[PDB]
Amino acid sequence: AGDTKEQRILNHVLQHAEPGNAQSVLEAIDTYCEQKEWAMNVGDKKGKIVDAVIQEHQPSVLLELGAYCGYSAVRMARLLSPGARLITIEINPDCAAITQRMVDFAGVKDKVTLVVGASQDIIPQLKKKYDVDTLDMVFLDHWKDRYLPDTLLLEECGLLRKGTVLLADNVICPGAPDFLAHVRGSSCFECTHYQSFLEYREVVDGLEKAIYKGP
Ligand SMILES: C[S@@+](CC[C@H](N)C(=O)[O-])C[C@H]1O[C@@H](n2cnc3c(N)ncnc32)[C@H](O)[C@@H]1O
Ligand SMILES: Cn1c(-c2cccc(-c3ccccc3)c2)ncc(O)c1=O
Ligand SMILES: [Mg+2]
Image (cartoon, rainbow, N blue to C red; front, top):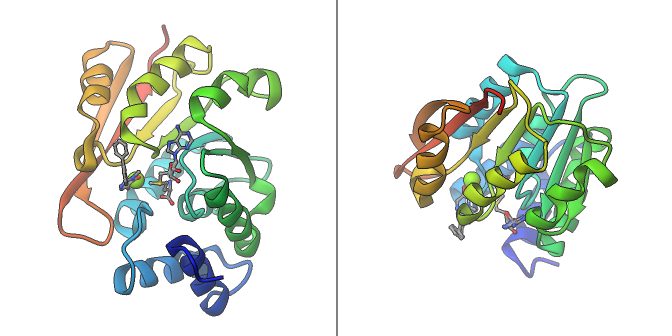
């Protein structure tokens, strides 16, 4: 179509990336967003921090909040082992449609379960509908005012265990100070900050890793 920025990001990938080649898809999205239209993909610089977290902790059951065009889903899915699952939750059904196409194009279809709906509604269904016991890792990257209540909801729903890894993008810009005060101030988390930059910009941003210690 070319009507929305999201459709234009996808079109660019369709025109320039190699199918089945996750790295190719990510480079194409990053190039377009660096050069033509800024978009809220975690991007390549903060992407390397995301990579490093996945490579250290090696999650088999991963949850992502906020899928957008599929950039981070592809980024994380490409590093996952055979049999590993990425469940990604996306509120905007038009973003979701782009994400499925992006994931299919990149060759990581079988790693990904895309769910359309609000994280606050879908999180408490994970046990009942999606075969989840507890989560290995969660990537928080949706509207920043949802970080705190969704972390509280994840805990309450029984989805965190000793060693569950939370990784939150944008804890500086646009920021999530209430979420940070909670995880850093609670003895139930061990936290690490990764200072970086907002995607495609020179504005300072950061990620926070928070490891659940158990209740
Ligand atoms: C930063 S974008 C996601 C970017 C993506 N993680 C990446 O790096 O490629 C934020 C997304 O979260 C979605 N979102 C916002 N609130 C949500 C919620 N409560 N539940 C699920 N998705 C939500 C928005 O529609 C938007 O697509
Ligand atoms: C979501 N997001 C955004 C973004 C873009 C528009 C609005 C909001 C938002 C909405 C409500 C409360 C707080 C923030 C956030 N910018 C950069 C990212 O990397 C990202 O993941
Ligand atoms: Mg982000």
